[PDB]
Amino acid sequence: MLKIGVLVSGRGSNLQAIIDAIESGKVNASIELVISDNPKAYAIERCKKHNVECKVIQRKEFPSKKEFEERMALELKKKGVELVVLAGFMRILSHNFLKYFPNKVINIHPSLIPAFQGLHAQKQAVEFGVKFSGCTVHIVDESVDAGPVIVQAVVPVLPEDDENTLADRILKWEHKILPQTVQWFAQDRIIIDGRKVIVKDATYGTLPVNPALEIF
Ligand SMILES: [Co+2]
Ligand SMILES: [Co+2]
Ligand SMILES: [Co+2]
Ligand SMILES: [Co+2]
Ligand SMILES: [Mg+2]
């Protein structure tokens, strides 16, 4: 099975989606370790309920960021983690961490990047007034939600939508494209060429997900 590690900082609904997809047999992978930088994250409780190893590693426990990132990489390496998944993780990863997992660190972001990068992307979309938003699974690099794009899901925005209502609509898709991406990695179907990513034998040119979902 694909051995993956998940980094979290809060609620962790995206972690739950992966856990459920694995338990239902839709994703051929195992979560070898979950790392939370927040001791009170609900994500930790999810790990307890599903018997998923979880470790709390806090930034304040290290003088430098370099140390902090090194410890997290090492702990993942010790578990043979092949794919690192950020699910609600709030720290910014640098080359110190990324160099260990070349093109093997992914993240789920609630917007159609490069649009609305950064924090509160759903609220950004609503205040801006776009008619379409959505979510993106991308490879993490030194940019702020500007790395290689694996898959995106488009979601219509309503005139009366507020941050929470739109976020809720986008989240339904995040819970689908992130687990699907994990499965694609598990199937050795992720091909990288430059900053472009292609999924082997996947269906392209589709709505509302491109490439189209397969396990959902
Ligand atoms: Co273990
Ligand atoms: Co735990
Ligand atoms: Co983001
Ligand atoms: Co609208
Ligand atoms: Mg999450």
Image (cartoon, helix red, strand yellow):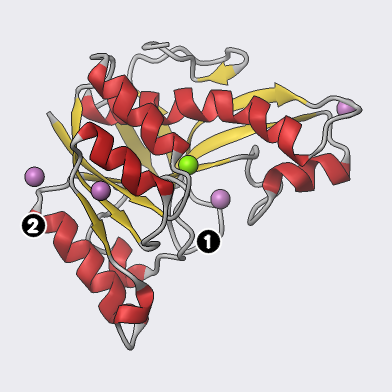
Q: Quadrant of residue 48?
A: top left
Label 1 amino acid?
Answer: Ser
Position of residue 146 relative to residue 202, above or below, is: below
Q: Nearer the viewer, residue 25 or 137?
A: 25
Where residue 63 sits in the image (x, y, percent)?
33, 88
SS class of the residue under badge 1?
loop
Q: Nearer the viewer, residue 185 or 123?
A: 123
Above or below for 65 versus 183: below
The answer to which image quadrant residue 134 occupies is: top right
Q: Residue at x 22, y 63 (%)?
A: 73
Q: Residue at x 76, y 45 (%)?
A: 123
Secondary structure type for disc 2: helix
Marking on residue 143: 1
Residue 137 in the figure: left or right of residue 133: left
Q: Position of residue 201 (x, y in %)?
A: 34, 14
Quick one: label 2, few (<14), some, or many (20+) residues within 10 Å? few
Q: Toward which corner of the image does residue 24 lie, by quadrant?
A: top left
Q: Amino acid at mark 2?
A: Lys
What residue is at 23 percent from the left and 72 percent from the top? Answer: 70
- Residue 86 visible in the shown view: no
The answer as to whether callout 1 falls within 8 Å of ligand 3 is: no
* Residue 63 can be seen, yes or no: yes
Q: Residue at x 30, y 66 (%)?
A: 97
Q: What residue did someone put label 2 on?
A: 78
Q: Which mark is residue 157?
A: none
Q: Give the camera-side residue of 86 and 151.
A: 86
Is the CB of mark 2 within 8 Å of ligand 1?
Answer: no
Q: Quadrant of the N terminus?
A: top left
- Taking the image as shown, residue 89 lies to the left or right of residue 6, namely right
Q: CA distance from mark 1 to mark 2?
A: 27 Å
Which residue is nearer to you in this view: 159 or 46? 46
